[PDB]
Image 1 (cartoon, helix red, strand yellow):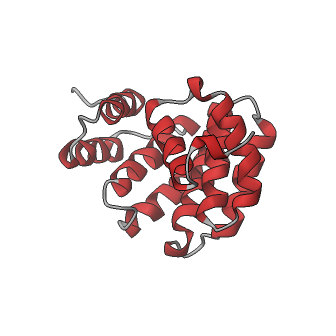
Image 2 (cartoon, one colour; image 1 turned 90 degrees about the vertical axis):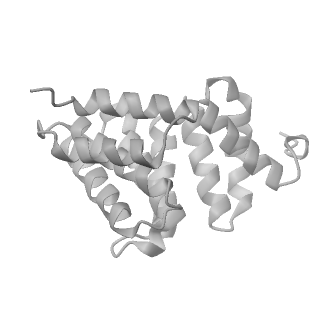
Length: 184
């Protein structure tokens, strides 16, 4: 009767986000529709539920605390269903959530979010995404020294980062005084 596939909804929302053409209304509509969609018990469904809740929360400064908990809960559900889904994307998501906003989650642990990010790097060193998110976490938690090798790996393969990821990396590098000071 026209109900959207959650995975396809996610891809459409992510396309808008990449373009910068997502409004609050677009993000909220995606959240409502994935919530309404039937759960097929897959890790993918749960990942999408978490990711879309996360995008809505991100558009509210990560201060939509109930949405952060919905993200946390569905990321854990996804991991329980298949911890290898999308090369551990749900574990990476959960790690980033904790390093950035763990203090706003009852069962979150900010510092242990770094362990999740380390786990993803250990399993999937080939993806600069993983190095970028690990570096982001170390920096967020005031521990720049271990971030530098990860920054160097992310910068070295920056052509494989999404536009959003490149802007994130470039912001971290601007904050340290410029990419020219990494001295990889």
